[PDB]
Image (cartoon, coloured by chain):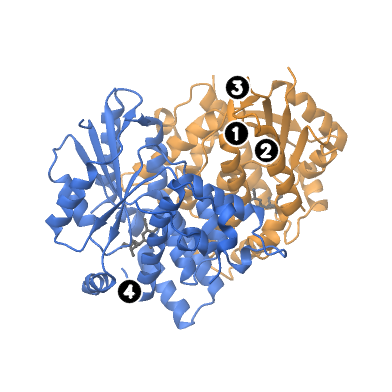
Chain colours: A orange, B blue
Amino acid sequence: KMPTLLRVYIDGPHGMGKTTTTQLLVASRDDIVYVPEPMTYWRVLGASETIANIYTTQHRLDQGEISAGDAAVVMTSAQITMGMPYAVTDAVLAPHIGGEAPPPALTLIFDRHPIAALLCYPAARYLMGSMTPQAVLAFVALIPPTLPGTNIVLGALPEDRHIDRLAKRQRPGERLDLAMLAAIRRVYGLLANTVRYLQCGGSWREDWGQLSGPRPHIGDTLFTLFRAPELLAPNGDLYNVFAWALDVLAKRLRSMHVFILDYDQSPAGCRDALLQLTSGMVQTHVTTPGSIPTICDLARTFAREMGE
Amino acid sequence: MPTLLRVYIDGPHGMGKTTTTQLLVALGSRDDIVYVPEPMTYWRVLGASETIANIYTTQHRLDQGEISAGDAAVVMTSAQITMGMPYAVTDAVLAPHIGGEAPPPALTLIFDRHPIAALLCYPAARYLMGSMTPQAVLAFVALIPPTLPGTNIVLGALPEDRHIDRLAKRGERLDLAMLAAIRRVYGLLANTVRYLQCGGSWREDWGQLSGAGPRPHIGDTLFTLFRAPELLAPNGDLYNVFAWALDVLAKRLRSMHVFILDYDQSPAGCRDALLQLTSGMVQTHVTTPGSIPTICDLARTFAREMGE
Ligand SMILES: C#Cc1cn([C@@H]2O[C@H](CO)[C@@H](O)[C@@H]2C)c(=O)[nH]c1=O
Ligand SMILES: C#Cc1cn([C@@H]2O[C@H](CO)[C@@H](O)[C@@H]2C)c(=O)[nH]c1=O
């Protein structure tokens, strides 16, 4: 039987302390790798200062200097750039991932999952009037299939403490935007409810009627974001093309494993929290003997080339 | 074990893919072969407004120099994301129904285009047109869904003079430059599958770049497009992130079953030519037994909602 792998995706909204936490966890250097955020790709390789381009566009939209449509085309392109290292990495990793599986051979810790750039952030900008809901569902359509052992760590942090940390940890080109903070915090909260809804037997088509008046309520999941008028026939029915994208979203999220990390503590308190959380995460076998070292290389090389 | 035949008619626009497809479906029955048309309705209305018209106008402005390459690029990328959405969800909802490769087929699905048209060929062609970055092309490439077994793709031959003629006959604008680009791109794609089925290996042949049947030279595959200065490290090699996107391209293309159809004939000519060619096409099984009418509903639903 092949070596076992543990994949761990540290996600949730920005500004809770997810970079310093795992930086602290980025400290044996051989049997566990930390794939950092592809900052260099964001600022240089894919495009010039993408983050700056994102926050400026939202701002200019806010000031009424540009229109909702202009802001959408810019936002949509940028989200393509933002997402690409997360997309390639997944594509090359996938063949190495086997079935589910006692300490593991290799632990991979990623800064974020593809659904950050393919679902969560697009959905947030939609709530911010800077992306059409059709684009969001286009990104959703391209969400890679959910491999086994997809453990996503999401954050818990009270809004005020979050604003504090966010203010002290602003990436280059970023503007402190409390409406975006609430957009993203709400998207990620809805995302956690969405996984519980799907796992408890939730069927979106069954409860879709309830958006008009032992699991969450559909109005508390991400499905509620797509009762958008753009997506709807004259008689209020969802177009089938959009409904199929919801079927996909449902399929992808139902099989991810969600773990909540309380960030409301000290940097190494978060670290220990992350280690405690691992005992419940799902390991997978790899698919070939030389999968472990191949994975290790991809990881170290991603780090070196696109890490901050 | 019921079986299925999926055939995707692709290639540059203005050849007769659509007519030929319809003639072909018109020979089966209202129960054993189904047309999946181009989602023209999605394109003009549902996903956005007059996307085809926005694409061709944007290119015209870039040419005319009324807009920068960058402004054209964000419009083209956004438009392309929209263009490809209905292909992406269709693939995603079909995938679980498709089994291993495998007499007559229970169902035949004739598609008007494959996902890679919107996720690769038109992006690459817009890149050659100077209205998309190579980075974004690779972003679309990295999002190409895993290639299902039994992926039969029918590209088209047609002399360029005859092709120009057909086009000049007919939301678009007569762009002969674009036609060269898209013809060249689909030419490379055909070569690229051939190059890959012949055990070709782009990493080992990369240094050879500057400027059925036998294995093509890499300079005559899609790989040639991505020796662009934006993609090259100080050392003159590709950045790994781009190399990995190219690995994905090879993995997606190598398993495809490519056929060429000659469009230098009459409509019924093409139909009978395409009908002959199907004889040598790979069928697959299906997973559930009730997969077949499920798949049938989905195609008629798609056609009814997004065709004309
Ligand atoms: C993933 C991701 C994304 C990150 N970001 C930004 O990148 C930085 C990552 O912390 C922040 O400025 C902000 C969260 C996006 O704007 N879009 C994304 O899709
Ligand atoms: C699929 C598809 C795509 C079609 N098109 C266009 O659709 C138009 C059909 O009228 C043609 O100009 C061309 C086929 C794109 O420009 N990009 C695509 O990705």
Residue receiving disc 2: A295
Secondary structure, mark 4, is loop
Q: CA distance from mark 1 to mark 2?
A: 8 Å
Q: Do the residues bearing badges 2 and 3 touch, measured as CB atoms within 8 Å?
A: no
Q: CA distance from mark 2 to mark 4?
A: 48 Å
- Residue A100, numbered label: 3
The subunit carrying tag 2 is A
A118 up-or-down from B187: above or below: above
Q: Do the residues bearing badges 1 and 2 touch, measured as CB atoms within 8 Å?
A: yes
Residue receiving disc 4: B173
Secondary structure, mark 3, is strand
Q: Give the quadrant of residue A42.
A: bottom right
Q: Is residue A63 visible?
A: no
The disc, 2 or 3, on the residue closer to the chain's N-terminal end is 3
- Residue A96, numbered label: 1
Q: Give the foreground label among 1 and 4.
A: 1
Q: Amino acid at mark 3?
A: Glu
The subunit carrying tag 3 is A
Q: Give the foreground label among 1 and 3.
A: 1
The subunit carrying tag 1 is A
Badge 1: residue crowd in 10 Å (few <14, some 14–19, many ≥20): some
Q: Amino acid at mark 2?
A: Ile
Q: Amino acid at mark 4?
A: Arg
Q: Do the residues bearing badges 1 and 3 touch, measured as CB atoms within 8 Å?
A: no
Q: CA distance from mark 2 to mark 3?
A: 17 Å
